[PDB]
Length: 123
Ligand SMILES: [Cu+2]
Image (cartoon, rainbow, N blue to C red):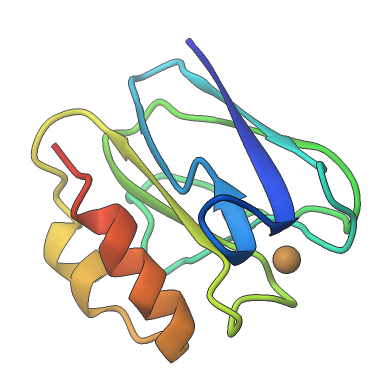
């Protein structure tokens, strides 16, 4: 249905952080991105995106909403704190076609650290 993601300087998970960092959703489902902390945004990791999905990037300190219809893995990052490891992951539907790629897509060490972490949450 609807899924709220907080964008945090600091959180229970760590520093520069999407909470929740992983989201299971289904077609039609809505992702509300929410500026709990200023200085963040949410851009698409295009080497983690189902084919047919439009690239996107949000204005800093402001809100954002993505709509999901296409199954698979949607990768997201915060543009200025990408290399600080601030990333998220949304899986829609069973056995995502872009699975291996998520695991293999080249990104900042810290981003990759947390990506694989939200990746082990896939079902
Ligand atoms: Cu950030």
